[PDB]
Amino acid sequence: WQECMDYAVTLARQAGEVVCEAIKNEMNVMLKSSPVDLVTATDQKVEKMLISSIKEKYPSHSFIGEESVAAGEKSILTDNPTWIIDPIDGTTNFVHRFPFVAVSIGFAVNKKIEFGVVYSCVEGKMYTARKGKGAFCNGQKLQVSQQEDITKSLLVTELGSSRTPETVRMVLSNMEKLFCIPVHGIRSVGTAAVNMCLVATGGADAYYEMGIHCWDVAGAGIIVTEAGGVLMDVTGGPFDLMSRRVIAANNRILAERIAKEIQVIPLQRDDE
Amino acid sequence: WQECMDYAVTLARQAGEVVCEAIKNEMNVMLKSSPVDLVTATDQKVEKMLISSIKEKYPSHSFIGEESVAAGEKSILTDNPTWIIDPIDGTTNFVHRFPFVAVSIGFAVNKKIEFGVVYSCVEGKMYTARKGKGAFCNGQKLQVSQQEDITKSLLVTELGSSRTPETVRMVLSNMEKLFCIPVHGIRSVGTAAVNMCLVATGGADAYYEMGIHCWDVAGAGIIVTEAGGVLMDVTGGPFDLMSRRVIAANNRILAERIAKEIQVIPLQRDDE
Ligand SMILES: O=P([O-])([O-])O[C@@H]1[C@H](O)[C@H](O)[C@@H](O)[C@H](O)[C@H]1O
Ligand SMILES: O=P([O-])([O-])O[C@@H]1[C@H](O)[C@H](O)[C@@H](O)[C@H](O)[C@H]1O
Ligand SMILES: [Gd]
Ligand SMILES: [Gd]
Image (cartoon, rainbow over all chains, first blue to last red; front, side, top):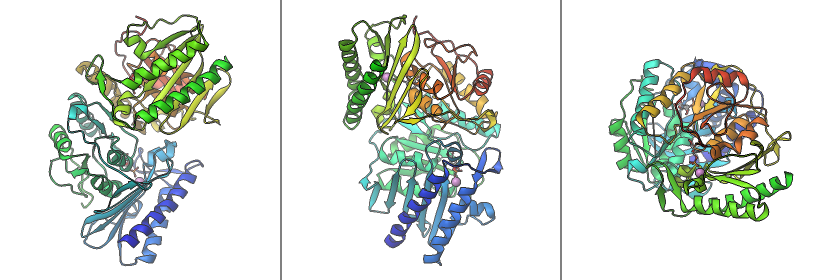
């Protein structure tokens, strides 16, 4: 899979070049599932580039992509080598020129992530990780923080793409519970993949969200764990990539403390 | 004042060097008024260095600084040339190595801000501005966004340092109102000066917060206005540097719409 990975890092650098030239030009901003769920022409054409470049070399592999699944294809994960692709994680940031947009590629065999690449192009930062070989940012090795005490922790989360009132209400009240423990603070940079990579560097101690998609987090998940962190469902159980919930933490102590405090928000799975 | 300014830029880059070597090393962390109100040896060290060098060169000038005030200096603003200094804005980020920390210097004469320097040392971004002469980042001219429609805007704000339940429930309540207009999103980078600087660049459309201090915002206020933005109190009235409250928006239409939406929290002034 090293060949696939070497190939992947090359693709991510290229698509990141496109995404970051587009960010300064005029854009066509269209609507997906609501007025706050967006897509531009660049999400679509970059996803097209990536899928056809991989298909060419690796014609037997399967794909799950955001804009593809939007175009009507289904998000069903099988045992076959599967590329899980977000062409632009942080599309609302992209549209606004808010300087955090990522290109994310995860690679799963036997329904398990083998390697991931997250390219944050505006910063010029390449995150990579392969199962068992560690996580790197631009060739330097990453490690999560050592904090085990929640009252001294710094968390990252997002408010989400939903504006359903009840949903919004549960999101804000889940925050209030954590904030009032108290923790040291909460941040949001606008993208799940980059939020997770900040955990891997040890910048933040933990990340949680409910409402993400499998393509948003498949690349960054293996980077956290190869950096020494942990992935967990919000029940405290094992991470389920298609479930739309994730806790990514420096360790199990903080991870279990967050699962304890927050309430579960009902969502449809990616595989439903 | 251009000499003071050229001086200011040199000081802020120097101190940014101190800050950004320190961030790599272990700190002993100290509390001030609460468990989440933090201070380190570097905050104190850097402020001391900064005040010494200025008053070496500018003996008649006054100073307002965060840690000075913590040592019992008072935050009364006169018409005298005054340097308003925050050695590290983002001390909680600093303690965590969350990669957004700034040195901030504003310079007021007749109790109006003449120039402002904000050095975000981890990114190597120097934001500067002088009344009537424009705003720049590393020699590149800044301009705020053109957004006049709140439903298509991206906001930045901070959850704040209070953990008083009543305050927190109002902070989140004000978030809910805005989120549900709806806006495109809300972000928090962890420092007021950098948040405001992202409004200046056009990355975000508006920033608001209640609970900040004069030193948090004295540098970045003129960077926003010289990029073409407006400052305004959350009440709708004019910006008061000592009031603990601020809206920094791209234009008057957004500033006034946000004020309409949110409710004011009672705060103790900086000059009381
Ligand atoms: O839509 P997208 O920009 O590709 O990805 C979204 C971003 O990561 C956002 O920050 C997060 O809150 C959402 O859950 C994601 O779906
Ligand atoms: O204490 P400090 O870190 O120097 O400054 C603080 C930061 O800018 C924070 O983002 C903001 O929410 C607080 O209101 C400020 O006081
Ligand atoms: Gd996306
Ligand atoms: Gd500070």
